[PDB]
Length: 224
RNA sequence: CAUGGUUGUCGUCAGCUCGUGUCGUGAGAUGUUGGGUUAAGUCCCGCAACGAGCGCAACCCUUAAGCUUAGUUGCCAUCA
Image (cartoon, rainbow, N blue to C red; front, top):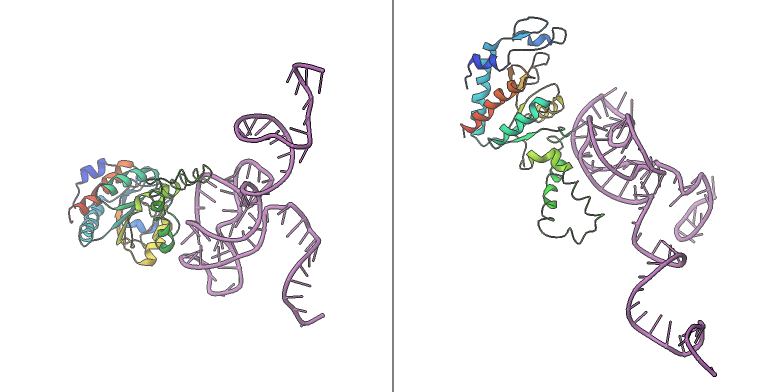
């Protein structure tokens, strides 16, 4: 669980935004404010970095899945790696509009990634012309562009770890409607009434993301 | 102007929607808009939509170069 401040504030984590762009409900987590920036109150992280953690560890261990979502350039990588390295899912490109709520339809396009990779592992690109084949090989990269790291999810993920719950808000609307409790990294500048286990931290420094998202895949590795 | 069948027309114009999801108190919207391009809702990219049907194109004829199979009634190079 627990993290040590010194790596926390060496990681970036305590920064924030301009004093103009700020949300009055993250006023409990601020600390001071230097040079137009707000500055976060790590000691409220460090109680909440873990309080997220040993919710993660509990949930991996009863069979849960845990969708990682993050898409802002900082996140797309450090979520694809660490979501892998514990065996969960993730989504890096467009959050396709409507995959949890409209799931029944977006599945069928997650099982047409597999009607196709069974046509080329057998023969059959010979029987079909070049004007019916040049198609089936970039309808394989659209459907893999977006749905790639999710193609082994059959039911709604139990929890969900979101990285920017303002760029991401398309998703949170969907989870908060299916009741899928969210864990997420709020910057300043964002709003915690929609989320369940907020992590008051930074949001732009790549290392700030990966460090924190380092953990939450540790703590599904271990309670497991 | 009680019908069924057949037929012009706008017009070969690029349209006309549906499931499921979301938005809206509702009628409705979205998708179908947007940056581009195309004869073409034709294609890419983006995007609360994700896909699908009828159209569009192509599969059909007849035209413009050849190549094997064939030589009457067609053709007449090399000969009377």
